[PDB]
Length: 178
Ligand SMILES: [Zn+2]
Ligand SMILES: [Zn+2]
Ligand SMILES: [Zn+2]
Image (tube, rainbow, N blue to C red):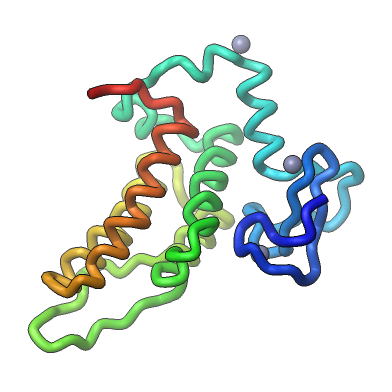
């Protein structure tokens, strides 16, 4: 097993996957690492199994169809994984916790959003469709773009949104386009 957390790349109190060499801090894994269960399989392994059980799940999909899916167990898992993929980028630190807004010449967003709030929402099963989760994710970056205007700090929102969107297309097998 790896000697660092797959998500935050630090050592500490780690839980090891039994089916692959990844390791996790308790609350870096999503969902939080389960109390018992021997053997234990991580989210990367659980996502791989879905694909292996239904190879055709990797054929291309339209985003509009994906968004309307109900949050059944397999779509819940895919959203948890997509969330985890964003936390895997160190630039996710800027979007993790509750923001505040007091900048000359800007007003804060009408509906603030941050990664830990989406994490809790997923944990508490507050999304009924994929669209709910993806809307809150995109809102994080859109709020940041609007607030920071022409400050070059806006680019952090662009950068982390690109990680989100690449992973969204991969995890949900969105049809490749030009
Ligand atoms: Zn970690
Ligand atoms: Zn694993
Ligand atoms: Zn099948």
